[PDB]
Amino acid sequence: SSETFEFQAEITQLMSLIINTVYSNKEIFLRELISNASDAIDKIRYQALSDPKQLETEPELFIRITPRPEEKVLEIRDSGIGMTKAELINNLGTIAKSGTKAFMEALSAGADVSMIGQFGVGFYSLFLVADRVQVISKNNDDEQYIWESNAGGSFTVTLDTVNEKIGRGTILRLFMKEDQLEYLEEKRIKEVVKKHSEFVAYPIQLMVTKEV
């Protein structure tokens, strides 16, 4: 039962810019998504300072990267606070737009795309390497929902009936661009993550398939 929503115009403008740009350093998306994951875990830990039972839906705090090469998909999972249906709509598509236009103005002047996180919109850097994204999220106060965008003017939010029901947190499922499948490889993922993983407080887990 998917509902369709319109992006704020400025968010559409930013996504079109990023999904089309020939910017050289596409690997920065991993730092930005890991940073957002870490912030989401910070939030649930902080909420749990005064309400420890909020952690019980998923007591392990982790960031997990799962390449799914047959589907040409990269998943970035956190056990952070998660987003409700209302938050997915609000935070990702229909307002979220203040740092958005300031960052585009900075880009026009020559700022590097790598500054995107300092404008608070690093999430949209995923479009450097992905044509489409599903954000699968479970907040303690709502059911699990799927937000899906292909960088158009519209996105959908759907009650999740197809993915694993996670305890708590968010999966960013990246449908990788055909020319960006290097980020599905263990060696490449490790190289990139180690450039900025030193001070991430939570374990960054790489799901690797070993043939016995």
Image: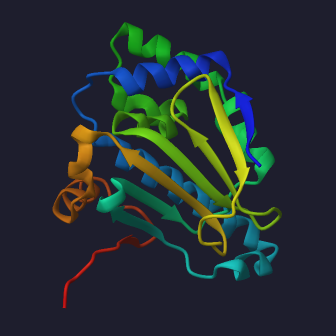
Residue 57 coordinates in the image, percent (x, y) = 71, 79
Q: How is the image coloured?
A: rainbow
Q: Is residue 101 visible?
A: yes
In the picture as drawn, the residue positioned furthest to the front comes out as 1
Residue situated in front as seen by the camera: 122 or 118 = 122
Q: Image quadrant of residue 142?
A: bottom right
Residue 165 coordinates in the image, percent (x, y) = 65, 72
Residue situated in front as seen by the camera: 159 or 199 = 159
Q: Image quadrant of residue 143?
A: bottom right
Q: Image quadrant of residue 29?
A: top left
What residue is drawn where x is 59% and y is 25%? Answer: 99
Q: Quarter holding the C terminus?
A: bottom left
In this image, 152 relative to 205: left or right?
Answer: right
Position of residue 171 relative to residue 79, above or below, is above
What residue is drawn where x is 65% and y is 24%? Answer: 97
In this image, 112 relative to 14: left or right?
Answer: left
What residue is drawn where x is 76% and y is 75%? Answer: 54
What residue is drawn where x is 21% and y is 65%? Answer: 186
Residue 194 coordinates in the image, percent (x, y) = 24, 59
